[PDB]
Image (cartoon, coloured by chain):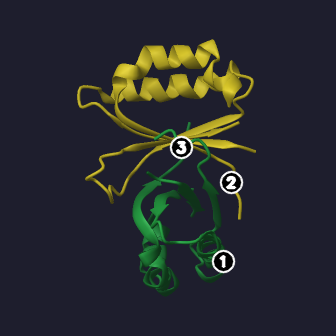
Chain colours: A yellow, B green
């Protein structure tokens, strides 16, 4: 199974309630994007690399059907102003 | 459950065989460290952004035990010349 890791920092203007609604909306995308099987998210507690400033993590389990899906594109349309930086990684987890 | 996410880029001199050995050793750490419950790793395929690899470790208090642990310290002592940069995040996955 294939995973997508999203690492992000929100702009300073964005409030806590706004972030909770951002993640809740992204989690509910699972029910309307057939490619999306699972989503978890989390906030970094240790701030080991605070020079970089990334604060949150999203784990999505599945990608082209998702990328152009209007729900996915629409989510990007609504919330793009929320994030100051963003890294995306796609990979197959192994041992 | 608490997860540790490690994002890294290797030095250009590091070879594919070395990286494979790096990850197999890191994965076997689950056998030596009681706090370490599970490990997966993967290589980013998309290159959307310089980071190339991810490691997912499954366990916050029992993270301190891992961090100080001689096997974890020893792993860093062996292999830290391998990586050019790394990010580390600790979080509790939720939805």
Which chain letter goes with mark 1?
B
Q: For the residue labelled by badge 3, is the local secondary structure a helix, a strand or a loop?
A: loop
Residue A34 locus on image (x, y percent): 74, 23
Residue A7 locus on image (x, y percent): 45, 42
* Residue at screen point 70% across, 43% down: A2
* Residue at screen point 71% across, 65% down: A95
Q: Residues within 10 Å of mark 2 (few under 14, many from 20)?
A: some
Residue beneath disc 1? B28
Q: Residues within 10 Å of mark 3 (few under 14, many from 20)?
A: few
Q: Which mark is residue A93?
A: 2
* Residue at screen point 68% across, 31% down: A63
Residue A20 vertical placement versus B39 (above, below):
above
Report how many numbered discs are placed on residues in the image.
Answer: 3
Q: Left or right of B86: which side holds B4?
A: right
Residue beneath disc 3? B47
Q: Which is in the foreground here, disc 3 or disc 1?
A: 3
Q: Which mark is residue B66?
A: none
Q: For the residue labelled by badge 2, is the local secondary structure a helix, a strand or a loop?
A: loop
Residue A12 locus on image (x, y percent): 24, 31
Which chain letter goes with mark 2?
A
Residue B82 locus on image (x, y percent): 47, 73
Q: Which is in the foreground here, disc 3 or disc 2?
A: 3
Instruction: Quote the CA–CA distance across marks 3 and 1.
Output: 28 Å
The quarter holding residue A83 reads: top left
Q: Nearer the viewer, residue B50 or A14?
A: B50
Quick check: marks 2 and 1 in contact, CB under 8 Å? no
């Amino acid at each position: 199974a294939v995973k997508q890791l999203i690492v992000l920092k929100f702009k300073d203007e964005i409030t806590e309630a706004q972030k909770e609604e951002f993640f809740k909306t992204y989690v509910n995308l699972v029910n309307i994007i057939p490619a999306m099987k699972d989503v978890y998210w989390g906030k970094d507690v240790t701030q080991k690399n605070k020079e970089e400033g990334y604060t949150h993590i999203v784990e999505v389990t599945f990608i082209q059907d998702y990328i152009i899906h209007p729900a996915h594109v629409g989510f990007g349309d609504v919330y793009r102003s929320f994030w100051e930086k963003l890294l995306i990684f796609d990979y197959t987890p192994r041992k």
